[PDB]
Amino acid sequence: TVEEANALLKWKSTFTNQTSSSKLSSWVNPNTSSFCTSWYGVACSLGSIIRLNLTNTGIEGTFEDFPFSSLPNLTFVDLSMNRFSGTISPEWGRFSKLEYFDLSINQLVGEIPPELGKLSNLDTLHLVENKLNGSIPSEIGRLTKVTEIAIYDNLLTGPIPSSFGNLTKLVNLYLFINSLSGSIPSEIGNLPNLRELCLDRNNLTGKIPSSFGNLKNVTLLNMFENQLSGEIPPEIGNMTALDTLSLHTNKLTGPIPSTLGNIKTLAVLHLYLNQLNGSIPPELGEMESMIDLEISENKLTGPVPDSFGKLTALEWLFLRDNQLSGPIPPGIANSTELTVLQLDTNNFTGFLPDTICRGGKLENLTLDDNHFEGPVPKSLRDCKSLIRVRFKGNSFSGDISEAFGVYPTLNFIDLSNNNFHGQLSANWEQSQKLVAFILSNNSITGAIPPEIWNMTQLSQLDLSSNRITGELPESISNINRISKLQLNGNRLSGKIPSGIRLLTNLEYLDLSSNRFSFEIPPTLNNLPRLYYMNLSRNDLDQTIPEGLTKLSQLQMLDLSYNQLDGEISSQFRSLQNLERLDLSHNNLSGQIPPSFKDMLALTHVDVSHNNLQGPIPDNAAFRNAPPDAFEGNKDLCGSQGLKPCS
Ligand SMILES: *[C@@H]1O[C@H](CO)[C@@H](O[C@@H]2O[C@H](CO)[C@@H](O)[C@H](O)[C@H]2NC(C)=O)[C@H](O)[C@H]1NC(C)=O
Ligand SMILES: *[C@@H]1O[C@H](CO)[C@@H](O[C@@H]2O[C@H](CO)[C@@H](O)[C@H](O)[C@H]2NC(C)=O)[C@H](O)[C@H]1NC(C)=O
Ligand SMILES: *[C@@H]1O[C@H](CO)[C@@H](O[C@@H]2O[C@H](CO)[C@@H](O)[C@H](O)[C@H]2NC(C)=O)[C@H](O)[C@H]1NC(C)=O
Ligand SMILES: *[C@@H]1O[C@H](CO)[C@@H](O[C@@H]2O[C@H](CO)[C@@H](O)[C@H](O)[C@H]2NC(C)=O)[C@H](O)[C@H]1NC(C)=O
Ligand SMILES: *[C@@H]1O[C@H](CO)[C@@H](O[C@@H]2O[C@H](CO)[C@@H](O)[C@H](O)[C@H]2NC(C)=O)[C@H](O)[C@H]1NC(C)=O
Ligand SMILES: *[C@@H]1O[C@H](CO)[C@@H](O[C@@H]2O[C@H](CO)[C@@H](O)[C@H](O)[C@H]2NC(C)=O)[C@H](O)[C@H]1NC(C)=O
Ligand SMILES: *[C@@H]1O[C@H](CO)[C@@H](O)[C@H](O)[C@H]1NC(C)=O
Ligand SMILES: *[C@@H]1O[C@H](CO)[C@@H](O)[C@H](O)[C@H]1NC(C)=O
Ligand SMILES: *[C@@H]1O[C@H](CO)[C@@H](O)[C@H](O)[C@H]1NC(C)=O
Ligand SMILES: *[C@@H]1O[C@H](CO)[C@@H](O)[C@H](O)[C@H]1NC(C)=O
Ligand SMILES: *[C@@H]1O[C@H](CO)[C@@H](O)[C@H](O)[C@H]1NC(C)=O
């Protein structure tokens, strides 16, 4: 009507920063046949506006001059995705016909007025992504026809009103990302039509109401990242339409209720980061639909039940960081769909089962810091789908080249501190995307296959603390992405290859405790990320090359326990980031260069058991050094443990 159109024009005249490419260019002629046919966002019935849809039209303004008293037949209102600021007036509750009300994604502030509860015909209320604060008024519980309430991502405080139990037609309730507090009212459990209940990321406390067992149609229950406490009520097992139950990151205590096995529809169960204790009920194996079972970071004890072999759709099983113990039953890995088996930081014992990867789809197997032992099952040898294998801290045994097959998509493997023996196979080269190869402190013997240096995506290679023999070839330069190279504590012999000079991504190089002989390559001068170099405990000889002083990021340089001789270069002053320097147990002669006074970052120095003489340079490391950093030298003199200088 002319009066509705004139009133909307007056509201429009108040908008700011309007671009004249606005859709509202079409708001000109208030007569019908303009108003009801060509005004953007306006739809009428019998010449009167019943729908106002200005979503995402770049309006900046407020509702201060919104014409509440001029639009009596307003039925559908969508003002979302604009730049409306200010508050939500009580006058919005005078639109008696309103069915659909959306002010989301604006910059609205202040409290929700109780008058919204007067909208007795409302079907949908959306106020998401604003900065609304205060408590939800209890009068919202008068919206007896509403089927969806979404007020997520606001600044709401206070409890969820008990009056929400009167919202008998409510289907979806989305209140996540707020600061709602108090206990969940038990009246929520008596909403017969409820399908989705999302109260996650709030500050809710107290126990989950046992009334939730009356929620026979709820398919989604998200209440993660709250402060819920007490035990999960056994009545939850009567939510027999649940597809997804997420209670993670709460303060729940006591046992997992055995009645969860009653929920045959349940596909996703997230209970991690709680304080759940006791044994995993064997009835959890009856959750026939379960795909994604995550109960890590709890205080569960006892063994995993054999009934886990009945979970035939299982894909992800997260149990890390519990106190589970004992042997694992073959059923734990029996799902042909299993892709991730995550058991780290428990106290499991015995062998891996022969069911593992029987479906040919297992990807991530992580077992760190358990007590597993025995040989690798042949079905894991033959598991071509593996991406991540983490066995650190267990005691697996067997010949390493018999235990493992070929893994084309392997990305990361850590076998540190296991008990594997044998020689490395060239088969590892078929993991062309492998970025970390960690085999520290096994009983590996024999040579490094030359194919290893063709694993050009390697970023970490750690074969330390084995009994590996042979010489490093010049083609070591081919692992040109390597950033951490740890070959320490082996029996490698021959000269250190010059090709390491081309490993310009190297950050950390440990070749120590080997039998390397002859000179340190004089071309190691161009490793601009190298902060750690350890060549100690070898048989390296001749002079320390000046190229090492160009390794400007070095923080630690350890060349101790070699037969290096000649003088310490005064160009060491160039290592301005050097904190720790160990040259002890060598055959170095002459004076410690006075240029060490330039190295203000040095904190630790050891030159003991050399053939050095003369006074000690003036820097803090030398002043703070204990007598044994100097002992065993020829004629050092001081101004500790040294005779004073003349
Ligand atoms: C638009 O609103 C007007 C004003 O409320 C409605 O007109 C009234 O209709 C009632 C019927 O409930 C009549 O008895 C009155 O004579 C009208 N009042 C006035 C002040 O004109 C109109 O029906 C509404 N139109 C639509 C399509 O909802
Ligand atoms: C909701 O937000 C408003 C706006 O920041 C808060 O309003 C302030 O309230 C205090 C005390 O009630 C007054 O002293 C200020 O002058 C108010 N500021 C404005 C801009 O109105 C309001 O307190 C908040 N409500 C809650 C419960 O936090
Ligand atoms: C591994 O899973 C299979 C099913 O995928 C289990 O085999 C079924 O066992 C039940 C007995 O409870 C029989 O009624 C079915 O006929 C079996 N199906 C097939 C295809 O054999 C097997 O028991 C599971 N193994 C373990 C160790 O849990
Ligand atoms: C059972 O497993 C737990 C977790 O893996 C072990 O606890 C760790 O023990 C080491 C060594 O004492 C500590 O450095 C860690 O801080 C502990 N981690 C945690 C998360 O507590 C525990 O030692 C194991 N029990 C036995 C008998 O080995
Ligand atoms: C098994 O672990 C790997 C991590 O190494 C997962 O792969 C990564 O997934 C993210 C997506 O979340 C991708 O952006 C990365 O590119 C993937 N990395 C690699 C190396 O592929 C993989 O999704 C896990 N498997 C399952 C079923 O969760
Ligand atoms: C360089 O590596 C050697 C091992 O090859 C580290 O040696 C340790 O040194 C301390 C004191 O010198 C001894 O108490 C340890 O017993 C040594 N360990 C071994 C396994 O021999 C040395 O610490 C490393 N240097 C730096 C700076 O990290
Ligand atoms: C106009 O727009 C800019 C940013 O959109 C803002 O700084 C200014 O406050 C706006 N309106 C005014 C000053 O009325
Ligand atoms: C408003 O228009 C958008 C885009 O056409 C549409 O997706 C939305 O459902 C409309 N809302 C109403 C209440 O008409
Ligand atoms: C709505 O709930 C309140 C308690 O919050 C109750 O007093 C009232 O009677 C309920 N509604 C009806 C129609 O009774
Ligand atoms: C689990 O927690 C309760 C206290 O909340 C305690 O009574 C019980 O002994 C705990 N330990 C178990 C069940 O092993
Ligand atoms: C491997 O190192 C661990 C500590 O990391 C040590 O306790 C263990 O004895 C080493 N391996 C063997 C076989 O001794």
Image (spheres, helix red, strand yellow):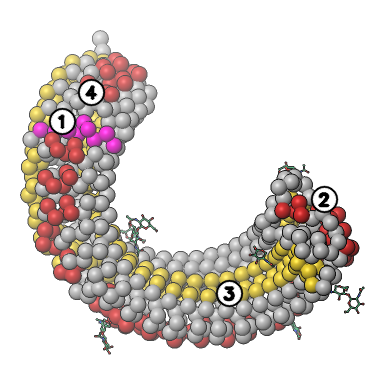
The disc labelled 1 sits on which kind of residue?
A: Ser
Please name whichever residue, 312 or 442, is drawn nearer the observer in this view of the structure. 312
Q: CA distance from mark 3 to mark 2?
A: 39 Å
Spot occupied by residue 476 in the image (x, y as percentages of width and height): 16, 39
What element does badge 4 sit on?
Answer: helix
Q: Residue at x 15, y 69 (%)?
A: 378
Q: CA distance from mark 2 to mark 1?
A: 76 Å
Spot occupied by residue 315 in the image (x, y as percentages of width and height): 35, 71
For label 3, the residue is 197
For label 2, the residue is 14
**Which dot, 4 or 2, sits closer to the camera?**
2
Dot 4 or dot 2, earlier in sequence: 2
What element does badge 1 sit on?
Answer: helix
Q: Residue at x 32, y 82 (%)?
A: 310
Q: CA distance from mark 4 to mark 1?
A: 12 Å
Q: CA distance from mark 1 to mark 3?
A: 65 Å
Which stretch did the figure color magenta?
495-505
**Which dot, 4 or 1, sits closer to the camera?**
1
Dot label at residue 451: none
What element does badge 2 sit on?
Answer: loop
